[PDB]
Length: 49
Length: 101
Length: 138
Length: 17
Image 1 (cartoon, rainbow over the protein chains, first blue to last red):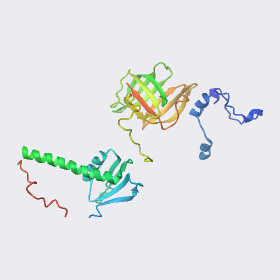
Image 2 (cartoon, rainbow over the protein chains, first blue to last red):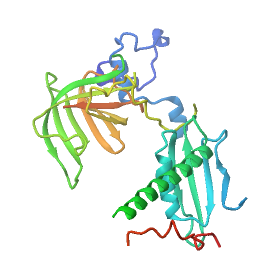
Image 3 (cartoon, helix red, strand yellow):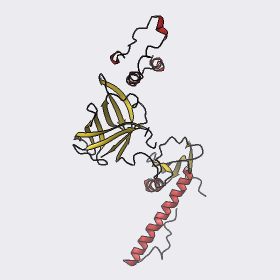
Image 4 (cartoon, chains in turn red, brown, yellow, orange):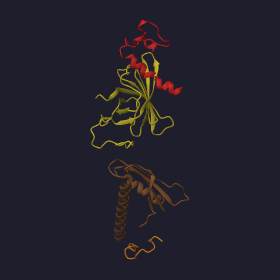
């Protein structure tokens, strides 16, 4: 995510605008590229655990 | 009326036909392969294949899966009739050639 | 029209059969896309490929643009794609990997015939779904 | 040779025992 310039949210965020999604400024291109490369769903993590 | 020769295998049969296994006793690769070829020449049939489950048993399970056009039983009947017609063609050609020589 | 996910013309560099008699692993580089490379396993008794020949390679979903669950061929007189292509395979994209910044590789298995496609900007076209036809014409 | 025997001879042995 950070190699694509956008934020790599490894740590949880803590600010006033922490509610808003940090992928809004990304222009729909590197979002779908990142989802193409790694797409880890919550269902997948829960199934693995 | 031979009620033991050919048997529909109900466990290996789909709802509303189109897929069935038939158990045929006292038959082997001879009929199995020719019948399978003829049935496979049916455009509605999508799966034909036989197996002799064990050599110690004079038995043959032939599997037919079709599309929705016809049933597996109808495919088997058409295949048997087409096998007969093929055998008639071969017999007629062989007889005329033997007579001519 | 809207069912093609990728389309490019490739110049074949290498065709090596490695201990095979009907499958070759061709290497082809794109034309006007200097970053796009292609490695593809091809049945060469159905589609023979020679070194340095032009291949128009297309990746598409929905080639034809019951609950029988068994694949049925389309009707003989069906106005579908692959009428203008000499060689068509059906496979699945099972891996997307990054080879560098702004450069990814996509891996397809066509029943074991592997294709590795490399490029940069395809993120809204190539996905990890079963629906993937490979269409090659000389 | 070249003469049919199947036509003139009824095949009894081909019946299922």
